[PDB]
Length: 317
Ligand SMILES: [Fe+3]
Image 1 (cartoon, rainbow, N blue to C red):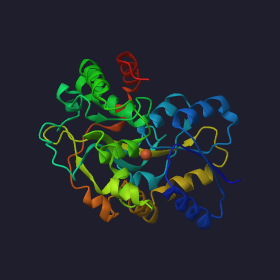
Image 2 (image 1 turned 180 degrees about the horizontal axis):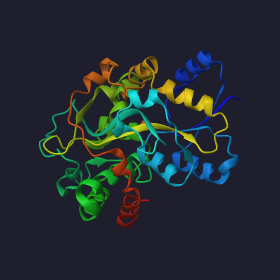
Image 3 (image 1 turned 135 degrees about the vertical axis):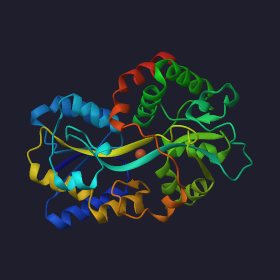
């Protein structure tokens, strides 16, 4: 049992990546998957005695929460610092992006839909869109971090108004993740879905013909193009403080930023690579170009508590 990974990622593409690491290094990987909230509690209760070496997330704020709970340890790697831009890794060297993703607003491009008035995140909360929006639970990392970014940019008053309006505008109570919101848009149960870009790729390229149809129907609004740009989040990685296979851990972290693995992440999981010398997959190119929010993801995550607070006060959960 040579490397223990606790991962909140939820993608079949990761199995190939793991196997590739094992074949390269001879290290066997023990892969545990659960919700980030459950992995953080588990690392908290296991403490110093945890078998965990690596914590992997699909969200910045999950990494920062683990950090701020003393659950991680710094890794100083020339390899990671050379290929990951400073804005996409912890100043204190305890977490590191492996990919980027954008949380966008999707519509059914196989319909005539006026998207002229759905340009910014704030537009989701607008009375005119009552009954026309779908979004997953406020307890989801993607949901919490998106609201954190709205607080970071617009402050808590506007953020609360936004959360209230979104709640009031939901076509249905939240059910499932991003792909279920996409299915709702395909089916005509809602006009707009808040979702991550890579799910569009996963759907368009799915083994399931029904999901291919859903994916093929989706058009992308990259919100806030006229101003601050679209919300970016990261999938990221850290060494746990509990790590006893630290050699292997640092090897795996560097491996995640290697050319072939960054290529798999965009080719097979439709995410944006962190490395600036890896070609995007054709599906990802097809999402189109867009302006990104320039706020550091670390600063977003500083507003995570107020995000959970607001969602609670407004009546989510
Ligand atoms: Fe995801």
